[PDB]
Length: 86
Image (tube, rainbow, N blue to C red):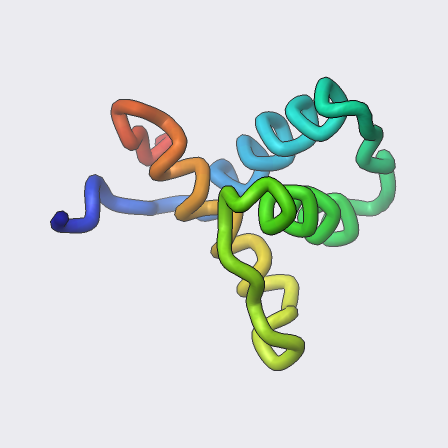
């Protein structure tokens, strides 16, 4: 299994993971808060680790960049065409 497609502007993939992870959480019976931005990113992350969508980062890699990166490769794989969101 070679790594499918390239990942350009991570920011768009993070946002799309806020969309899919946010709406999924909501429909699963939750509500992620409309708070600054990196807090919502981390909220989506916790939900996705619970949902076994991604693996838990250690407290050393529990950082805004690493969280966004988890969400990025998640949705990059989650899209069936593995689209770069460009």
